[PDB]
Structures are given as C-alpha cells and as structure tokens.
Amino acid sequence: AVRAQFENSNEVGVFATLTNSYCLVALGASENFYSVFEAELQDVIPICRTTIAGTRIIGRLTAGNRKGLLVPTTTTDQELQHLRNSLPDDIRIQRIEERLSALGNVIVCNDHTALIHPDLERETEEIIADVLGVEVFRQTIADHVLVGSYMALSNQGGLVHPKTSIQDQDELSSLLGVPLVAGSVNRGSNVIGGGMVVNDWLAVTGLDTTAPELSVIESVFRLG
Image (cartoon, rainbow, N blue to C red; front, side, top):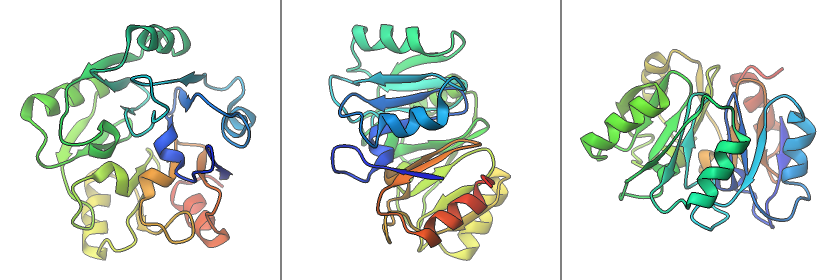
C-alpha cells in the first residue's frame, strides 16, 4: 500500500476513484497525488484526470466499480466525453439524481455488491444495481447512514469504522462474502472511505496513515 496527498489534504478518497478497471484523479497539482497513482498503475489500467461538475471533488461525487460509473446530474457534457474517451469502452457511465448527500457518501461498492444509505429512493437503488451490476443492500456502519464515508471495499476485503461492533463486522462480512476488519486511516481517522481508495491489488491512503494502519490495510485487502 502507498500514501498520497492532494493539495495538502490526506483525504485521498475525496479526490480519487479506484476500481479494478480504471482510476479517476482530480485535476490539480501532480506531486504526491497523480504521480503516486501513475507510478503504481502505469499501463495496467487507465488513469483519467478529471473534474466533476467543474470541481476537484471527484471521489466524493462519484461511485464506480469495474463495470460502471455513477456521476451527478451536474456532470458536464465535456466531462462525460472525456471520461468516455479515457475509460474502457465497456464501462457504463450514467448521470444519477441523488439528493441525500454526495454520491460517494451514500454508496460503497465492489464488483459484486453495494451497500447504500438506507433512505435512498427506490428508483435510485434500481439504477445503482443496474449500472454497477451489483446486488444492493441498505445498511448502516457503526450507526452512520453515509456508508461511503465510513468503509473502503474491494472484492478481497473491507475496512470499516473503528467503532463498528464485532457482531456488525461479522454480519457485513457474511453479506459481502469478504473478510472485514475495523480500523483507522490517517493516524486515527474513522472516515475510512474519505481517507483511502482500494482495488484488488493496490491501496492508496492519506499521508498521515501510520505503519500499523498500513499493515492492517495490506492484510485485509490481500495486498501482500
């Protein structure tokens, strides 16, 4: 696992989206952000440097997996055309209306399953399942409804808010079919989905993440 920082913020998951088939990175200063992803991913999967709705908040505004990418209704035609040009031709890229919070705060997904905020509209849940090609469950994490902020998930493992009970960890693990643990990033932050991104072979965490936290990440995501 590696470390990165975007314009002085260690909240890597707010400014990037990483899947098993592509990576999105906020437009901005290359140093210790795009460069980190490129050093690990060069050739392997494409990296798209993008804005979303004209902003740099591109991880928090999107949700995606290796099959599909959900973006807000305010994503521009420029941005959609650029995403489509950079990403594999079989990715389904869809604008979606979702008013509870930012998209990336209300969904956490891998290539098989998504957990969502329990109050999303039924139509929203249908579009998520269709575009991402996943089974969907309404869930909370450590009593939080903004599940995308509080979990990071791949097909290999997941990391949840450090206060998640062991009973809830076991329930979520069994539902997802992957090992889970509770832990922190960025030197004790519980905003796991904000602080890191992950796919089946790479994790990128904020710069303050400590050695024990990186060790937990490497183990549960099967990165070593």
